Image (spheres, rainbow, N blue to C red):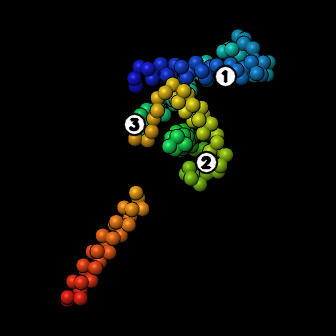
Amino acid sequence: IPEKLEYFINKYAEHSHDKWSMDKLANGWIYGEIYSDSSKIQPLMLLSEKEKEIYRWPIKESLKTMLAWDLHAMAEMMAENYHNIWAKKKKLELESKGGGNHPLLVPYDTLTAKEKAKDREKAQDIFKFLQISGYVVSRGXXXXXXXXXXXXXXXXXXXXXXXXXXX
């Protein structure tokens, strides 16, 4: 990973903190030492410091994925990355602890239209954050050509027919 992408990760963390703090001021949450969800006190003003820390790694993983591998296509591909790693973890823990079957034990195509939006929300967020800076990424006539190919095929067929007539 390059160093100004190292910058970009810190800038993303900062702006995610700014959006979360916008939510904090919108809902009127106030900081405190004690941890609780009903009394409206937070040690990092719901989220623990670890519980914001954890969102640091999946961005790096998805970014490595985009580096090793249009806009909506990359969005749904990052969303599929998220859902695939989520399904992998859930399947491993199910086969580990003997858990029951989940309704998400299906491929990404048969799935419903709602989880689509659920997994594309943050994908669109990080993609906005990506295009704000300037870094542009991608995946990494025809009729005339088809007509020409058909003509060549017809010529070959005519040659074959002439040969057959000779035979």
Q: Residue at x 74, y 18 (%)?
A: 25
Q: Nearer the viewer, mark 3 or mark 2?
A: 3
Residue 9 shows up from this direction: yes
Q: Crowding at label 2, few (<14), some or many (≥20) Cα neighbours within 10 Å? A: some
Toward the viewer: 48 or 24? 24
Toward the viewer: 148 or 58? 148
Say above or below: 155 vs 161: above
Q: Crowding at label 1, few (<14), some or many (≥20) Cα neighbours within 10 Å? A: few
Q: Secondary structure at mark 3?
A: helix
The tag earlier along the polypeptide, 1 or 3, is 1
Rendered location of residue 95, percent (x, y): 53, 44
> Which residue of the protein is positioned furthest toward the right in this rendering?
39
Q: Which residue is mark 1?
A: 20
* Residue type, mark 2 in image: Leu
Q: Which residue is mark 3?
A: 68
* Residue type, mark 3 in image: Ala
Determine the image quadrant of residue 156.
bottom left
Determine the image quadrant of residue 43.
top right
Rendered location of residue 40, percent (x, y): 77, 18
Tag of residue 104 = 2
